[PDB]
Image (cartoon, rainbow, N blue to C red; front, top):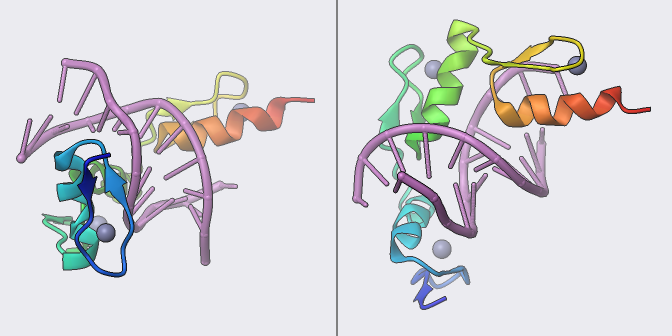
Length: 85
DNA sequence: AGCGTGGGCAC
DNA sequence: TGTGCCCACGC
Ligand SMILES: [Zn+2]
Ligand SMILES: [Zn+2]
Ligand SMILES: [Zn+2]
């Protein structure tokens, strides 16, 4: 990991500089992506997309066992295991 | 549960 | 780099 975060209080190191560039947003407080519905700002475009589903009710991920739908794949993943014994 | 949000990284 | 997934933790 050649790329160290230059912020004094931070000890994170990255394999790729582009990842350090994304990381630095934490320290600069930069949130370039805004939700046009509630005007909230987010650090990443991926997180803005899933956030928008909280407004639209879009839930693309259905449980294979019971059909319950979720906005995110990881939510469905956390859910499916409840069907275990 | 609902969902913010960082880290890894494919493309 | 931008875009956007998986994974994982947190409240
Ligand atoms: Zn840092
Ligand atoms: Zn919003
Ligand atoms: Zn289910």
